[PDB]
Image 1 (spheres, helix red, strand yellow):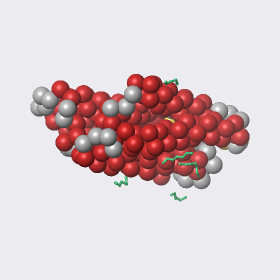
Image 2: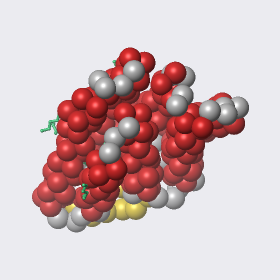
Image 3: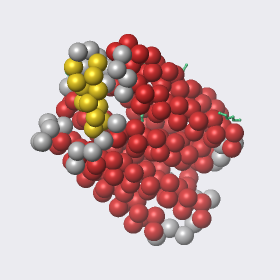
Amino acid sequence: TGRPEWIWLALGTALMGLGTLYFLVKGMGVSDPDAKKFYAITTLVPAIAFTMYLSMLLGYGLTMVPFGGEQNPIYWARYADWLFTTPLLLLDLALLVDADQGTILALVGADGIMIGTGLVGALTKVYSYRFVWWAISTAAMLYILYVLFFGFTSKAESMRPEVASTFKVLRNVTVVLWSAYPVVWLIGSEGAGIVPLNIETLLFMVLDVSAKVGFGLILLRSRAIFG
Ligand SMILES: *C/C=C(C)/C=C/C=C(C)/C=C/C1=C(C)CCCC1(C)C
Ligand SMILES: CCCCCCC
Ligand SMILES: CCCCCCC
Ligand SMILES: CCCCCCC
Ligand SMILES: CCCCCC
Ligand SMILES: CCCCCC
């Protein structure tokens, strides 16, 4: 089919793959128990992204949805990725600052709601109702971010300096990167249809690699993950 976005799906496959392999090799060599947990979680993240990026490349996870008088291409496979990857990233953050079980449950619950409503949105046929689901999803996201910013940061300042400092970086990457997703969806093929699907994929590829491989590099190279 040779769809124009394929190139970025192919580069995302390769970046996710390499990052998975690198983290696996590095994880395999660690014996510290606490470090191992971070390695497992953090290797699985780009691994999942890899599979989803590869699938999309090979033309799975793509469906046509009718709205605004057109058949719009929607990659639902991203949601299958983010369903598991986003809460895993939150888990890494939560274990870093030793967050309470209840906070974790709430964050993972809110995250499910973000991704589930984002997907309903993406698949909705009434143009205006697409944006209602988008709004509910953005809300859930903002809850998350609030918690990371106000709750976790506060928790991190009881910890050793390298733990507080590593957390702040990861928190800052997370806030900046995550906050861009809803904007992309809004202006792109799922929303207003302004940014073309080729460029939108580029944007999501950049954000995904940054949010998983970038995040992962900073986390796993830090001294904070040793118990
Ligand atoms: C590795 C992938 C990451 C870190 C993906 C993050 C995705 C989000 C923060 C998605 C947020 C969305 C909304 C807030 C509303 C509309 C739909 C979503 C799912 C793109
Ligand atoms: C009301 C949402 C505010 C989010 C702040 C996150 C840094
Ligand atoms: C404090 C580190 C800055 C990250 C911002 C761009 C991801
Ligand atoms: C992080 C995005 C907040 C809502 C959309 C603003 C254009
Ligand atoms: C104490 C956390 C409650 C979680 C329900 C979403
Ligand atoms: C950031 C998107 C700009 C591409 C042209 C609509």
